[PDB]
Amino acid sequence: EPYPDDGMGYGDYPMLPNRSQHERDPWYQWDHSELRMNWGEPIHWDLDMYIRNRVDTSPTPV
Amino acid sequence: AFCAPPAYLTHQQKVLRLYKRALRHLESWCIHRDKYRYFACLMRARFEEHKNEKDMMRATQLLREAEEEFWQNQHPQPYIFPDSPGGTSFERYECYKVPEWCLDYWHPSEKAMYPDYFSKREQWKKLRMESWDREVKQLQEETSPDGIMTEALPPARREGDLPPLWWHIVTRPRERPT
Amino acid sequence: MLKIILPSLMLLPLTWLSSPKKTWTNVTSYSFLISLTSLTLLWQTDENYKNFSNMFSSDPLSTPLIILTAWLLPLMLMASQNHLKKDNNVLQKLYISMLISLQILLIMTFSATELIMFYILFEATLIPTLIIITRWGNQTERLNAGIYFLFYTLIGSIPLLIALILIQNHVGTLNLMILSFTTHTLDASWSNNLLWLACMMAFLIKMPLYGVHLWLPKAHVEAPIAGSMILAAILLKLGSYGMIRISIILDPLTKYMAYPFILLSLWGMIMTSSICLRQTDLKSLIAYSSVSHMALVIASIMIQTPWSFMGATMLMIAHGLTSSLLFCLANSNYERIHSRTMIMARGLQMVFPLMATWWLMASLANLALPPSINLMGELFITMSLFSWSNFTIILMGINIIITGMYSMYMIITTQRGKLTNHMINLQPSHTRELTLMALHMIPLILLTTSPKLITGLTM
Amino acid sequence: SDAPPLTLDGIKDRVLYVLKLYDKIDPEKLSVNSHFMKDLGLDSLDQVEIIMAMEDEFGFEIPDIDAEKLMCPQEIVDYIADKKDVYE
Amino acid sequence: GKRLFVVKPSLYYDARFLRLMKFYLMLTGIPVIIGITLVNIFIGEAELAEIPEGYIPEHWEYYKHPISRWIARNFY
Amino acid sequence: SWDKDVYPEPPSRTPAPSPQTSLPNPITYLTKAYDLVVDWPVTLVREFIERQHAKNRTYYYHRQYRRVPDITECKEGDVLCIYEAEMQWRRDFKVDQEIMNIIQERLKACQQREGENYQQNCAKELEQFTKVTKAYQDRYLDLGAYYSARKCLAKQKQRMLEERKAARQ
Amino acid sequence: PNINRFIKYLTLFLITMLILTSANNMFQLFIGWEGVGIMSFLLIGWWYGRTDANTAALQAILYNRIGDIGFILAMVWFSLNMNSWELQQIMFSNNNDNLIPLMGLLIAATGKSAQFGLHPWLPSAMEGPTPVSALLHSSTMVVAGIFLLVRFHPLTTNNNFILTTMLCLGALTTLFTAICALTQNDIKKIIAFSTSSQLGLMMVTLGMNQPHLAFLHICTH
Amino acid sequence: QLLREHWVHILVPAGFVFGCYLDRKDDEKLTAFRNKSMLFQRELRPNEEVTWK
Amino acid sequence: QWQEDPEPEDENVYAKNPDFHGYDSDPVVDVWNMRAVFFFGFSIVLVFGTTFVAYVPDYRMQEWARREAERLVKYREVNGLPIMESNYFDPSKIQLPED
Amino acid sequence: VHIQPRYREFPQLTRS
Amino acid sequence: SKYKPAPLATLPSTLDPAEYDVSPETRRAQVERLSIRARLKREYLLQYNDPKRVSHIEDPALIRWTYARSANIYPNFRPTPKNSLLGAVAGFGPLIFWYYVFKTDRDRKERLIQEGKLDRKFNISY
Amino acid sequence: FLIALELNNLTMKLSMNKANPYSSFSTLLGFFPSIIHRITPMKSLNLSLKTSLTL
Ligand SMILES: CCCCCCCCCCCCCCCCCC(=O)OC[C@H](COP(=O)([O-])OCC[N+](C)(C)C)OC(=O)CCCCCCCCCCCCCCCCC
Ligand SMILES: CCCCCCCCCCCCCCCCCC(=O)OC[C@H](COP(=O)(O)OCCN)OC(=O)CCCCCCCCCCCCCCCCC
Ligand SMILES: CCCCCCCCCCCCCCCCCC(=O)OC[C@H](COP(=O)(O)OCCN)OC(=O)CCCCCCCCCCCCCCCCC
Ligand SMILES: CCCCCCCCCCCCCCCCCC(=O)OC[C@H](COP(=O)(O)OCCN)OC(=O)CCCCCCCCCCCCCCCCC
């Protein structure tokens, strides 16, 4: 699903869901272990915002 | 860790995962061992009471209600083992888990400091040389013509053969490298 | 000044007559001797200015720039030694000649006593940077980047030429000291306002000012390491020196024509620090950090406090050294992994401990660690800006916070964390590049030890 | 000094110790190759309890999918040895 | 016993660079530091004196340190 | 080497020791040991160094500049005497900077010497500092980065004109 | 493998802390301030393969940087109004309106001592090794802002608004940190919030005109 | 043959000597105010003919 | 497809020359260029030049201005003169305009 | 200094 | 007594209702996603465990991400009134805002100096 | 000391109790780390990328 054609330079880049890398399964041997991402899978537009050293979107107890 | 996740979690797997998570949060709340044993026996009794369900849509609804109750009554700080993700010792030694290919870049003097270990290292490298083509052929042969395939890998199918893609698993750094 | 210009000139026949197995050694050693000879301009035992001849002179502001250029030339050869090892001998000697031409023309540019000679040497220095970026750049965007850089700078520099010729016709000689002595006040008319803009916008493009800074990141990315050094460490400071030389004859209307450029500089260093936070290219991130630092230099030069001029001077020298060191570390990583991605190489602290140490000191100099000349420049610029207006401290604080954030984000995502174990083509270290980092970092320590050399004209 | 290293025999002895202490497993029919359902007659909840008992003894977490794969004490011991790098 | 190999990167090149850097720096500076210590122990250390009447001092004679006076006399 | 005419210091008034207790003073014991171990070899080395200095004694002089004509008697455009007056002004500016440093060191020394009585006994140092900073603000303030003898003269002329206009009424 | 590296890092932190403590002028105290902050960053991110450790070090750097902004504001104001960073000229500056530099020093002390608003960098900074936790975050670094306020206490005594907001901020942060400490499970986090609550007690004591009691509590704590 | 092999090593020192020579030529060219500055107007010593060369 | 050389792969330079110093492929030019950089970079520039800069005397007359400041303070304090006059220029030798 | 580890019993406390 | 998700606190994969009322097309979608994931993992594992490899492994996803974040923006940008207004406000409104702030402060300070009400008691290093 | 001793004995007592927002607030750090460390970096980096660089 691409970004809507609002003329912001996105184009055909997919709208990956706004989930950080913290929600990714930490018991899995990801190809990029720090990034918790595999090889060849699409990369979020805000990966540098959603890295584990940065903004977290994880579910909270309350 | 040593097994790849499937396409989806079955209902039985989800029930077991909910049971384990509920008992872990129960021990986080109870702290004391006798109290945890009492309330964990109560939780096991609840699961055994809801065990024998045949309609399975009522079972899915019961699972949804039970995990809703779990999210309402979960510990804000559940107990995490130190080596577990989110723990205290998690990824503590990744700074010491040096990959094995730097010994290829080691100086000949440093190689001469450890002669026997390095000789065993080229023995292992020669074994990898000899096994790579055979395991690539095995991977190409065992690939199904259909688009279905999982992340599982075949074993060695005859004598004198190694499992395909064995190098990164066998030669991984130790969890206590020093 | 001739005793520095002539042997640098004679470096070119040495380059073209040396053996192909001795050219790098001979030129590097003799250019180190050029820097040693250029160190004699610091013999200033009097308040008077070193006027060597009717054409060349040395100054408390011009001297550190000349010494910096003469010091960077052997470092330039060292950084250019590696990526030209598979290259033809004639093209290698041509590249060395281009760097030597940069060094010669920049010494004459900083030592010129005439603004028209300064302008001639200004885009006489523009030409070989174009040639270096366009020929020895790696990606396909080097041609576009050279076009952008050259035409921003030339559309800047043409009204400077018209303003210079008008000033020469109005006064008579355009000599720097004659202008400084018989400076006449301006009538604050529209002609004088447009003349002020004409003589300001060239150096504002070369700085670069915010809004017109777009040539710098692409030129720095698609440039080679020597082009990145020459740009980020000499050419922006050359625009700085141009504004400092030209601002003396622009009283009194600079006190209100300074207004849009100060605001542009403050908001632009905030903007570019934010871009440094959300930047995916290491060379682009260092380039935008350079844009923010030169925006601080704009703010100081335009508020025209003596403390601000000093802070601009020390920030010139400190930012040139630390930006050259940052581009060298980035280029070492680029020659390792053949990529410029910020996030691709992560755990280099493990494989390269000494290079990660150099990374750490370079970033600490970048984020203004005390008692370095970097922080002395930013702190004195802060003091002068707060004297100019008390509400500048908010923008300064936001800039410093995001500066620390992007420097530590650099360190964390390039050195710390788990190692990308798939990069098995990681050679340990070259003594050449480790020497390059050491020769970048030691003069920072020495100038921190003695900061009186780079204080500038005001004090 | 501290933290003595593990051994295959010690891991096997500790796993069989916990399984003997488990009330649903009689110690006379317990072996290292005894299956939890085929000849021990347990179920999935009992298996999860056994995994959590091993987890609480050895002070580290077996992940859920590997834990569901472990099904006899020999596989449990092999997993412990593989995870803690015990080779003798 | 039962000690195991520790996998480490090539520290040989970093150690060699540090050794060469220290060697060249000491090779040039230890004669310099020894000479500085000797000259400040023995000779120079010019003290402030009033200008005698009718005497025109040399430019280096306005400077304090012996090395500064020598450089000013020989090269400036 | 320094003189109390330009670095004034009141004479020290230390009290005589009157130890009421019978315990020995570890400070006095450690001080006597400190002299006997450290101060004697250090002063021996310094005496050897000083007699080597006396063996090779040299002299240097403090340079003095005669007064060139000031910029007020100096024609505009004639850049020779413009230059001479401007460098004389720059020299006097640097001298005034160091005078300010001297007064600031005097004020700091007064504050550290008085300690808790600095609000009363540093009245003379504070008054001298206030007078010299009023004079400095009258002569050199708000000149800008391109401060010069011409700019200083213009500021002084503006201040004199303002004072003359205020003195009419 | 890096026990010598650890020992050298602790020694460098001690040097920077002694510089910060014994410095006479604000530039030298500022050298000590950021040297302590940077060595805190390195010692928190000692286990540099840990993402949580790197994150905690980065946010410790962030809060210390906001404190640095407050310090820079105070330093610049004192340079412009008293021509020096020397504490003697500050003592002579005791007799005017010092609201802006006292606000800057208050912000700096809040950032360094982890009061309310800028608190959680300390319990995040617990991520590093225990001797780092003790020496850095328990005894020496956390009392640096309190120490700065003790240094500038003659200025502090003459401003009643500053004293009231110091007292209120200290009471709020010791209450909040004790509330947080009541239910934590990690023992290091519990005694870290104990450290922050005692720092709030010192901050209350500096809200009163009792700086020497605050320094006595610094040594005691 | 050493002078033939290492003749490239004299070009930069020759340029340095030439630059010093040209600085000396400029210095003796700009002598229109020698011993004529009002700051340094002094009577010539009998053992000298110029204040600076 | 147009004729074009294949993409080269960078080789492990340390494989054939374990004492590689970063300068040139063969060992002799590499080690001599290393020695030339070390001797001309640190030895006779970063130390000799540092000594020369350190022993430049009276740099922009800080020491002379200090001595002159002490002399002027002594003069004006033993003769009771003000330390600094309010006017740099003598008011008698300035001709102000009549209006 | 080194003592025998205990599996589930009370550890042998040294006198010091 | 219900958890409310947020952009910064998302809904859990066990509290969402989408995986309790499952569908065969969602099941086969998960199957095909696992198939693509396994194919990419197999390709990466072959390239990673290849001994004849003498370099790193290039990531086309990372290359695509860098190109999309850097070079594709201006070819794929079209001016709309929304982004025109956004660019105008984000490039000017802070500038006029800080212009008015600094202009008011400097005019007030200049006026206070002109009638002398502002006192610079020891301000000599401006 | 006495209040926390009797509270610890109550935790020793064999009864589960439903958690309250006071203990949730105390255990979850007062919600200041979660709330601030999620909303301020997200707004800062979102403003940076979406406005500054891109726009
Ligand atoms: C990189 C920046 C590019 C844009 C800004 C360019 C500079 C803008 C300010 C200067 C005006 C233009 C250059 C004139 C140079 C000489 C100035 C001067 O001497 O002024 C005093 C003079 C006046 O001289 P005067 O002082 O003798 O006035 C007469 C006074 N009396 C009668 C009392 C004696 O001003 C001019 O002559 C200015 C006329 C300029 C007309 C032509 C302008 C053409 C367009 C210029 C920009 C083109 C590039 C950018 C295009 C857009 C790109 C996106
Ligand atoms: C271990 C080896 C040690 C070798 C000795 C020490 C190193 C070399 C000296 C380093 C000096 C660093 C500082 C340079 C100061 C230059 C001063 C100067 O102005 O020199 C030009 C001067 C012009 O002469 P003139 O103006 O007429 O002065 C006569 C008196 N009125 O003309 C002269 O002064 C004459 C020329 C002599 C000074 C040349 C300085 C340039 C640098 C030379 C580097 C040489 C390195 C040799 C290495 C050999 C290795 C095998
Ligand atoms: C100017 C523009 C530059 C642009 C970039 C240039 C790049 C190329 C640079 C080439 C070399 C140029 C070096 C320039 C910096 C020189 C630093 C220096 O020596 O400064 C002098 C300073 C002495 O201080 P001073 O000048 O008096 O000023 C302070 C008082 N106002 O010295 C010092 O304070 C100390 C000197 C350095 C530190 C000492 C190093 C040697 C230590 C040896 C210790 C040995 C062991 C102990 C021995 C016994 C000690 C008792
Ligand atoms: C009674 C009176 C009461 C008064 C109360 C006053 C309260 C004032 C509060 C002022 C400070 C508020 C903002 C603080 C931001 C802190 C952001 C931060 O570092 O967050 C850390 C977070 C990850 O860390 P965390 O979530 O804690 O832990 C994860 C562990 N797995 O995320 C990260 O690590 C992200 C990495 C950094 C990303 C870039 C951040 C740039 C921030 C630029 C800010 C510019 C403006 C600053 C203004 C300061 C004003 C004081």
Image: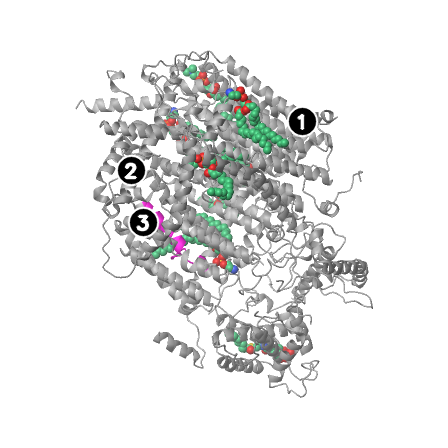
The residue that label 1 is drawn on is H9
Q: Can the viewer see residue C306 in this picture?
A: yes
Q: What residue span does the magenta drawing correspond to?
A: G100-123
Q: Chain of mark 1?
A: H
Q: Please tell me in which quadrant of the rendered image residue F80 appears.
A: top left
Answer with left or right where residue I81 lies relative to residue D23.
left
Amino acid type, label 1:
His
Q: Vertically, is F105 above or below A59?
A: above
* Labels in figure, total: 3
Residue at 53% over, 64% down: B88
The residue that label 2 is drawn on is F106
In whole angstroms, how far apart are the C-alphas of marks 2 and 3? Answer: 22 Å
Coordinates of residue C358 in the picture (x, y in percent): 56, 45
Amino acid type, label 2:
Arg
Q: Please tell me in which quadrant of the rendered image residue F161 appears.
A: top left
Please say whether residue K41 is one of the residues in the magenta stretch.
Answer: no
Answer with left or right where residue F145 lies relative to residue B44.
left
Q: Please name the predominant secondary structure of the magenta segment in the image.
A: helix
Asked if the beta carbon under badge 3 is closer than 8 A to the nearest atom of ligand 4, the reply is: no
Q: Which mark is residue G152?
A: 3
In whole angstroms, how far apart are the C-alphas of marks 3 and 1? Answer: 64 Å
Query: Is label 2 in a helix, a strand or a loop?
Result: helix
Mark 2 Cα-neighbour bin, 10 Å: few <14, some 14–19, many ≥20 = many
* Farthest-out residue, left: F169
Coordinates of residue G31 in the picture (x, y in percent): 43, 46
Residue at 62% over, 38% down: I38
Q: Vertically, is B96 above or below B36?
A: above
Mark 3 Cα-neighbour bin, 10 Å: few <14, some 14–19, many ≥20 = some
Q: Which mark is residue C149?
A: none
Asked if the beta carbon under badge 1 is closer than 8 A to the nearest atom of ligand 2, the reply is: no
The foreground one among C47 and D61 is C47
